Length: 67
Image 1 (tube, rainbow, N blue to C red):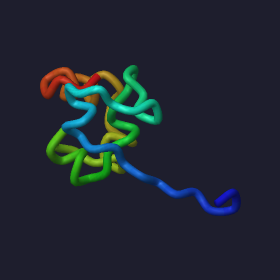
Image 2 (spheres, one colour):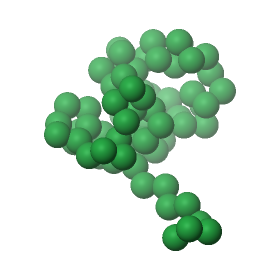
Image 3 (cartoon, rainbow, N blue to C red):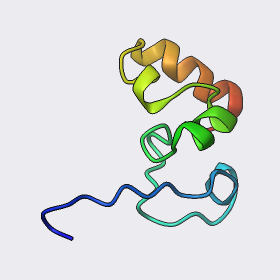
Image 4 (cartoon, one colour):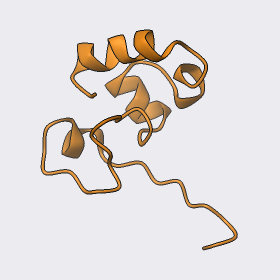
């Protein structure tokens, strides 16, 4: 568990507007959602936004209501 990092995404719904966990950071939701969640939450990818602008990428988050 220490040597390997288990990347687990939190249910977009449960966090998109529901008593979400803690691993889920509010300041930035795009860091805890996989392409699937990313696709339905931001319509982008962790590897897409990862390179795209920080504001433009955010521009979408607000559009969906994540950030």
